[PDB]
Image (tube, rainbow, N blue to C red; front, side, top):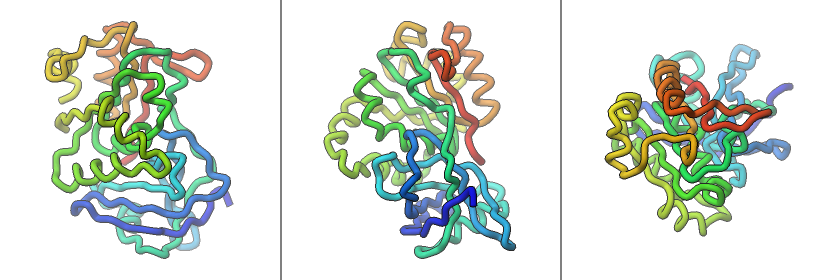
Length: 246
């Protein structure tokens, strides 16, 4: 009842661990790029769900999600075996903290991600309002594998009704690979050398963080020392965070 029952439209194994699927989207399901919803399946007549960031942008006809097999838990195992035509549960109330409006006006946007933290940014980098209010966007990730990069490359060019975004992304979006190390890279300044960019300041730099608990603790502490403040609905700031879904 708190879920709608979507139909799986396409399934993809980009590597042995990385799996994506697209499915039908409820007619009431509005969201902002970056948000998540509950995703799962009816198992033993009970809904079995977990939070997944919506990968697709809000102007795409279908939804998209992806999954990384790590521990191969009950849900991940069953999701990885979805077939086109299969029923899937999609929560009706999307939500999340990666909210651009909770960032004060600025020049540069950093999207700092590890593992599945990449997922909500596959959606945000296709949000046109990002490029209307920022000069530059940097996305840092931990993808290294052939098939993982092929997936990001596919996302990058999937722009239904927004083909003019192709030139804008090419101009403004910079991908920057790290290692399962970004904290260190901010600490040594090497992040800001590789890309010739000034180190974090509350004057120009706005940040989004999606990654592991440890990554968020260590990296926020580094942003604090540069004098950046966390944003909130009631009070926009310099950074926002969300724990990566695993």
